[PDB]
Amino acid sequence: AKPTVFVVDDDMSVREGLRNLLRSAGFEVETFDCASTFLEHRRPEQHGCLVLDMRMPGMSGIELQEQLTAISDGIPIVFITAHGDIPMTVRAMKAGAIEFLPKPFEEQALLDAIEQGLQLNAERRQARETQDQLEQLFSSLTGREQQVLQLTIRGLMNKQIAGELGIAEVTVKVHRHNIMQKLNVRSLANLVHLVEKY
Ligand SMILES: [Hg+2]
Ligand SMILES: [Hg+2]
Ligand SMILES: [Hg+2]
Ligand SMILES: [Mg+2]
Image (cartoon, rainbow, N blue to C red; front, side, top):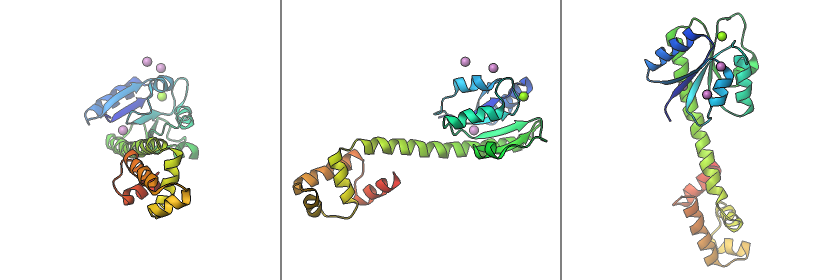
């Protein structure tokens, strides 16, 4: 999807200033003056980075982050604050913080953090799509096929698999053919990689 920077900050100058900065850099931008309007619109499939104010009406920045943690939305966060004297908590850092930046911010520092965040989002999403794709491929196998797969990745020959399970060799052959097609692999090497991957 399009790289989108979500900007959450109650202050108009921040929202407009960042919209302009981020557009002038090739990012789509979405802004919210509240945490809950963000959460209401948030789709965890949207590729992006969150730039987040500490203090806003309603939920604070940390409180929004707690919601995102709770629902396993792993979007990366660049925290911004006008009160640099108040440190981030250890928990706020661990829950996906890219960086903690002051307002007013160095434009380039902010841009570098967002670039860092987009790459971490791209990576995270790829590892999500892969796991998702592999659960659907593996879930599409029958119990019988599962039994054959388990022995196959143990290096057994069809003859030995047949004897172990009490089925005909042709039955094993056919199960093996169907496993390859279901899991979309053309070699025993790639079959074993896939099972280990998942
Ligand atoms: Hg709002
Ligand atoms: Hg809305
Ligand atoms: Hg981003
Ligand atoms: Mg604020």
